[PDB]
Amino acid sequence: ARTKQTARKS
Amino acid sequence: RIRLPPFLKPGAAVEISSNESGFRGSWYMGKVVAVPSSDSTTTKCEVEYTTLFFDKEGRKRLREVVDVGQLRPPAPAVSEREKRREVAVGDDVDAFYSDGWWEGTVTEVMGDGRMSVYFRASKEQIRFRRDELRFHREWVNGAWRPPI
Image (cartoon, rainbow over all chains, first blue to last red; front, side):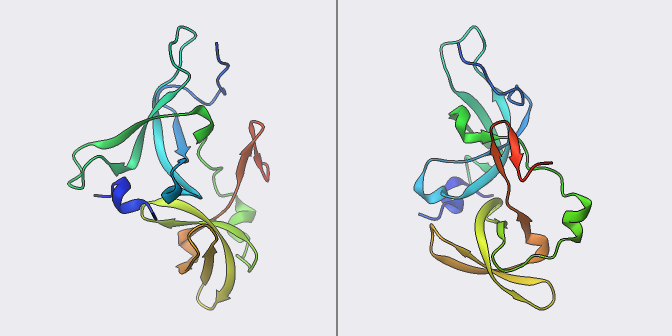
């Protein structure tokens, strides 16, 4: 599932 | 002490923006879990994300304490002219990507309803189908621009 770690771009 | 915007109440669906550089230009869908009461020690709200989780195995939706100014209501429902609107170069759009909406600008339209979108903050150039885009709107002074 998506997390901030795998959503953020930097 | 603080006069909350009327849309902000426990249970309310919202779009959530972040202050973190890696989230510049994004809106993630979520819901309000708690707000400052007239009886309150905070000025902040707690929200729960709809598509972001604490853990990658997805047991618990992410919750965060955020500033009121990070929240806006769900973007207006796509009207009937807006379904008739062709997306054009120069249009400000949000693209659905990594399960949230990211603001960019259409730089090229190709056939079969596909477009290329430039993202300024991340210096990215990414192709999307029409059904992955929405026309960008801003929540300003308690109302949408362009309005409903």
